[PDB]
Length: 125
Length: 64
Length: 50
Length: 62
Image 1: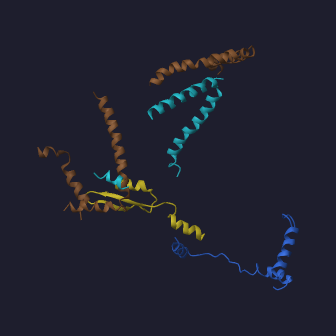
Image 2: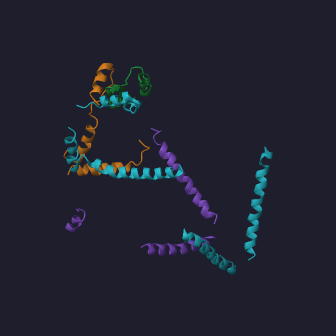
Image 3: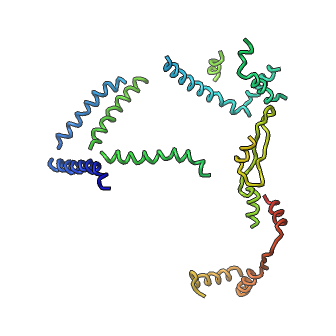
């Protein structure tokens, strides 16, 4: 339908006119203009003065910062556990642990805690 | 499989769009003369600022 | 024909592997095979057992 | 007969190869034997098979 594009055509008319009118200006003329642009750098320098010079929300920002720090710490620590399979130090460690912990079924261990569940504090207070 | 490259494709879509925008941004430009001076001046200030800004753990270093 | 027959045995007629696992209370994880003779895809067979 | 990509070149190369190899002890005998071979290979024929035997053989692959 022709009548749907009336507004688009009306807006597009303006683009064509000034495209031709800008070209005509240049043909009618230049060194003095260049000098002014260079002086404009002073405004950039003036704007360069300011540029050169350059209770739940608080808890949330602190939480974010500490979370990032903890992630970094864990990432840095994992490097030795990665090589544990051939590092000699991890043979002294994991031996000290066993010596200080005088057929363990892990599945059995979990069920004991699960059965107590969410009444832990209630059953001890 | 075709469905294990979906993340890579989605991330790679954004590369093409930016590549097209730069062409238009450069084509819409003699403002380059004004543009260059800003960097030419800021570089000196940045360089000046940078220039202005310019037990066992001890026995081990001594041993080394 | 022999090459294709060997390839079919290797890939199992193109249906893929069928090894799986189960969660049994107390006993923990155990092995489970989802193969069947009717052609039901793995994740659909594992639906009813869960 | 015709239609190939070059006929003289192949013949003029085959003659040189036949002369060279003889340096089956004379150039004529090399030409004669080259065709005796390449034609004596007994061909194989297809035959129906029992399904079970073939599946057993294929299973010993993989």
